[PDB]
Length: 290
DNA sequence: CCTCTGCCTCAAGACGGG
DNA sequence: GCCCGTCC
DNA sequence: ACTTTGAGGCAGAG
Ligand SMILES: [K+]
Image 1 (spheres, rainbow, N blue to C red):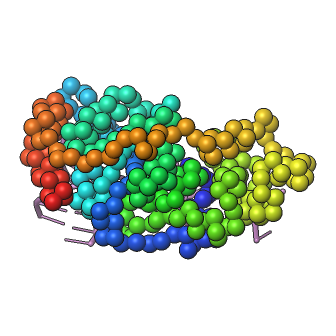
Image 2 (image 1 turned 180 degrees about the horizontal axis):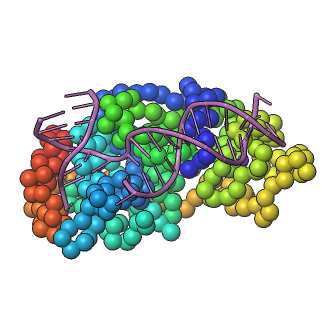
């Protein structure tokens, strides 16, 4: 994500962070990064050193995680759309089996040209969902107006939901969106390096004073704060500001009734889940729809 | 103050019975 | 409520 | 990634 950004916001713009009750999200739609979440399931849902799996050794940890997490959100009246990345390893088989499961649950999903986080942001911008619920601060860096942070952790711990508001962030820092991108690069982004010596304090000052990365190097003393060689900040700046994304007007998001017999055939027949648990999950899914 | 860096420890996904 | 054992 | 791995606290040097 962005190295330090949540702590920085809590340190300098805490009013951009709202603590809200899970009950106030009832009826809201939220975009969720399927690629990221599959990966977390592959790491966490383990037994005796291995993922869960059927008799033939096919992994089911991603399905276990995605089935019950999705039911849990719907039971809270939060209607999710999952976004799959575009251009422990998450395979194509993981993706396709999670997509199959979600159709069978009646849960929508979209495929993203490139970065799921950015395309999640594009759904928020366009008003197609209320927020992105992801664990990546870079959603804010991609321009997303609202980001629900640690939704599942808060749900389990019966804790209030941290909700980051990009507009209040810019207002407290005195920064436009373009200038906020450059800050996040200085903090440390996935795309390129950060200047050694320049931490969260020094980064905010220079951005507020000078307003752009290229300006910074000119005013910076090269001897004291040398930038790394062939620094790709220009390209990273371009990846955040104008990312390849899907069209949020393009696909209608619809939430359908779950296809129980096909879910039994697939989760129980093939993947060898317990039939009682799958029916019990479906029943809660039906009740959630109301 | 400000950034490193190194040394430490401590859940982690979800459900449900006890 | 909180532990833990178990899920496949 | 639980027979491990990252964050997050904390303290000390440049
Ligand atoms: K740095």
